[PDB]
Amino acid sequence: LGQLPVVGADGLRPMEQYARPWSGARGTRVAIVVGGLGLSQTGSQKAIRDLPPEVTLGFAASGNSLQRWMQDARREGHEILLQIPLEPFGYPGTNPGPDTLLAGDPAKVNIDRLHRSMAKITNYTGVMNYLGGRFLAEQSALEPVMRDIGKRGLLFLDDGSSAQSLSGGIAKAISAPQGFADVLLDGEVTEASILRKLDDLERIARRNGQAIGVASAFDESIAAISKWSREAGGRGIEIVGVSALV
Image 1 (cartoon, rainbow, N blue to C red):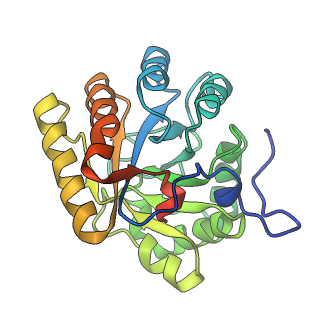
Image 2: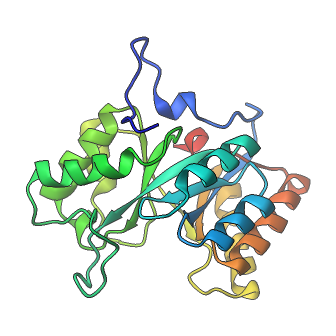
């Protein structure tokens, strides 16, 4: 903790070392990421209290008590991702914070910002974008970032909120482990909507063999996701960590 993730001398990657184990058996698999941990203290407490350990947790780099929520999550057995603030379209009106990676800045300034976020927690398998509408569409901005992440043995989860995102193509070009979320579960934060989106997730997972859903740690999201993930096994669905799928 306080250090940057690296591939070990033996070649072991963070994405292997901190992966949540799963059955290994054939069948439909689903990963669900609930992000935003560290932003609300009561919201983070509820997330840890209520979600089963199979739910992957995204930690906000700008969050507070990150070490506390890190230790609680890993104690319960959750796989963890680090959320990296990236430049949205509404910048600087919409500002995620001082460590936000910016499309126009040179590679070394963004890599320093990335490294500052990376050092705030440990034992995560990969990174995911927070926002990044502007950033993800810019090859010259995204490529050095994805190369740094890729070389440290981390996976990159793109939340899919930008259709113009270049992370899939860049990752193929550099051989980095990457995945797109299939479903945003809580674009509308109501019980009825989240249940419909969880049905979408199941449908896509059953057809493709696997799928990834993403949500934030809103009270309605936590309650709906906790209940659904606990009941998923009865319908031949194993909930696995993101690393198992990417």
